[PDB]
Image (cartoon, rainbow over all chains, first blue to last red; front, side, top):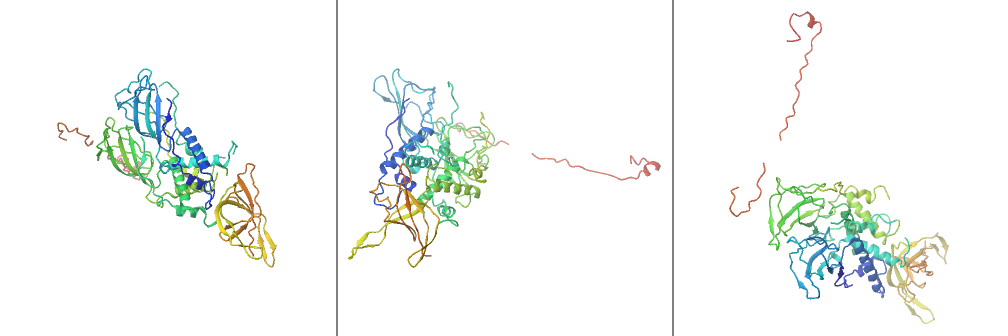
Length: 195
Length: 192
Length: 110
Length: 45
């Protein structure tokens, strides 16, 4: 289970023109763009910080789940939570020659546990010495205006502290701080066991 | 179980004019444009409708779930509900056939629940999970809210405005003490 | 660290020279900056033939390299509406260089 | 309902009065002197 992404966020979809207005930088100057390589450099470092604490995706890029053995009998939970329209389930063998399979797999969409849920009582069988690549586009929406706004506010509260202090300097968190906004987007799991 | 909403709230229904009268009026200076303020109220509505499981502007939802909990139940999570629109019951591909009888919406702030008539509830096909579109929330405007819940939005959106990053600064009826009576109090972590 | 809450218009005057070696000031507006303003102890001051009313008003803006428009220079001034804040000097508050100290007067003629 | 052959018939219609049980009171008054000198069982009448 590798879970690398196919494409990344293009950078034009990040609200640098709004994160600049959040930082209270400056309005009517002839410069107005001296931090576009910087304000975008901390938005990518605060989205990807919250994607690791909440296991969310927030921009709906395309992923690829390359694994070698199905975890359980039929369900196969996906790590990244908000999923939609699994593009292709291919079933590779020992060397290349991938053959796509409709495969009777169906993707229950749920932000609790995004899983595949085989409908023929078994997931399609993996060849000996072969992988399985699930190609899917997981995330909230294609633009920034489709995010849940409490999660998008935690990105601005966090990327503004990477801006306003560069090295690791210690800073009482506010009622709904950074941690209190992402703590209803985290994954609440209580299974450390064999099944 | 996904529960995405149908349409977002327009912003012309949010009180960006009444927020600056909370923010700097009576005491202060008669600062930022409407797009900066409106980014902070819906960032404070979505922080309180997540902590209290409410809706506050009464937009339309779609709850699409794959298995009912009981056969006379499936409580709905977003709390103030009114007028469940349709109970669509798709098959696999989905020619998308709705049903129009068998259940009664019970409007209740405690457990907004769907409670089918008798003992049998509409079953689900193999693969064709059932979706519910309902319009949950207090009122279409902002003047239909409970005022203590509407004040804690203003007390929180003035916090997101007047201090930008996660910095330093509890009052008797604060933000937490006002939304502590709109939160869902449940003590079942069990099987049913 | 500062709470940049108030909006101030930075103003640089373009200096058209006259015939006799001096310049002419018109004070066109530069961009708008956000800054906190902290009043000192204020009292009247004997002006020329005016009884002025001054206050210290240390103003904290964000910083910039010296060849940038976002640096307030001491020949500039702030303005919140019709309140002219002068600039006495800029002095680089933090050790890392994130913020500046402007120094104003805001002397209304009382 | 008259089940058709291939209809997939759906569920039909499944089908408290309280009796508060009030109280009826009689409290007749009688002088003690009377219950000793009369020949009739005023206790029983």
